[PDB]
Image (cartoon, helix red, strand yellow):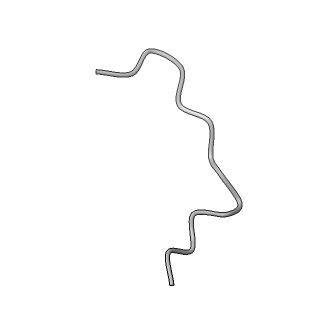
Amino acid sequence: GRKRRQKSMTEFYH
């Protein structure tokens, strides 16, 4: 799993 979730601005997977 993932304890710390950081919203990646590069989350736009082209």
Examine the image and state in which quarter residue 10 appears.
bottom right
Q: Quadrant of the N terminus?
A: top left
Instruction: Report how many numbered discs are placed on residues in the image.
Output: 0
Report whether 1 appears left or right of 11. Answer: left
Q: Is residue 6 above or below residue 14?
A: above
Residue shown at the point (57%, 74%) measured from the top left: 12
Percent x, y of residue 2: 39, 21
What residue is rendered at 51% in x and 84% in y?
Answer: 14
Residue at image location 62% in from the left, 46% down from the top: 7
At which x and y percent is residue 3? 44, 15
Q: Position of residue 13 (x, y in %)?
A: 50, 75
Q: Is residue 12 above or below residue 7?
A: below
Direction left: furthest residue: 1
**Residue 6 point in image, percent of width and height:** 62, 36
Q: Residue furthest front?
A: 14
Does 11 sit left or right of 1 as displayed?
right
Vertical placement of residue 4 versus 13, above or below: above
Residue found at the far top of this picture: 3
Q: Residue furthest bottom?
A: 14
